[PDB]
Image 1 (tube, rainbow, N blue to C red):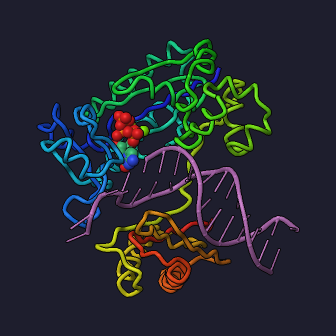
Image 2 (tube, rainbow, N blue to C red):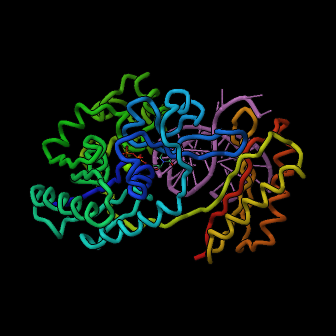
Image 3 (tube, chains in turn green, purple, red):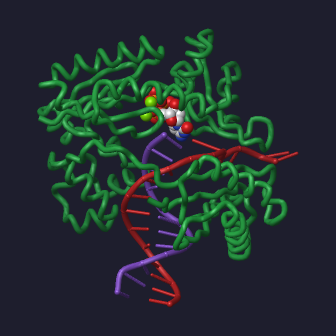
Length: 343
DNA sequence: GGGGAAGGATTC
DNA sequence: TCATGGAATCCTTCCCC
Ligand SMILES: Nc1ccn([C@H]2C[C@H](O)[C@@H](COP(=O)(O)OP(=O)(O)OP(=O)(O)O)O2)c(=O)n1
Ligand SMILES: [Mg+2]
Ligand SMILES: [Mg+2]
């Protein structure tokens, strides 16, 4: 057969805060990244469902949130803490399948093909899984089940929150036909608008255009991706993800183009980036700057060997110098990203 | 001879 | 200070050796 079971934790961060403070439950809760630039500068990382009903969701400014919802609990985000809960939950999942792809802090794919003989037993597995996370972590999750990762992902998107959905073989075929292509994982705002403009609305539409014409408009990779899902021939195996880069970006108190004013922030970011590397060694470093009008600009360097902390400090100042004498705009956010890990 | 670096798009 | 975090995947483009 080939059964994938996907698990996505409901309103994750905000839910961990309710579990930690069960008096929050049933009322609006908003998890915030406060940038420190003025009282309440920053964005919302997520909010529970009672906040979302009023428009308060992930990505908006805290300032927006607070004008639509004065009276909500606003909490700073403590990713560490959510990461500890996630790991315990990923270890429960591990118990239902050896073959598990941890996709992020709040979601994982299980290949349950050897555990379960059909979609009916998969569902029942969906449910002991749900009852088990609830019993052990007091966290509700949504489960999607289907023949591959993507449809398993779509199935969970359609059933959230606290849901479980199967998209069996006939349903795959219906969805390829009626599912708005904007709802396919990995297809964003810019790509969807490109596709509408050409009048491609459904996965099915992609089988009836010059592949070469699709590829032009959206890139070879997305074309191929969509077409393979539209042919029902998508079957990327469940695999261990290997982290490829680590980094840190911060917001300055104020916009500067002044190197001595910027460096305490760059060095702050190297030191936290280096600490999180823990034992792995990068051959590439990039300095990333977000300018006052929000363009992203970066300069990097790839060395034939690993970059020690001391080389990071001197390469990063140099790369900052290159940014500063290229672009004339002032800098609002500065950070560093290490990648191309040895071994 | 590509290849590497900068940016694009998406998602966390 | 004067909405627009932080983070990490591909992938694409385009310039120079
Ligand atoms: N712009 C964003 C979007 C999400 N997240 C974080 C907060 C979420 O708790 C977590 C997982 O994202 P989801 O899309 O799964 O959304 P939630 O889990 O919050 O809600 P739900 O899945 O219930 O829609 O990632 C973030 O930091 N920044
Ligand atoms: Mg998720
Ligand atoms: Mg979620």
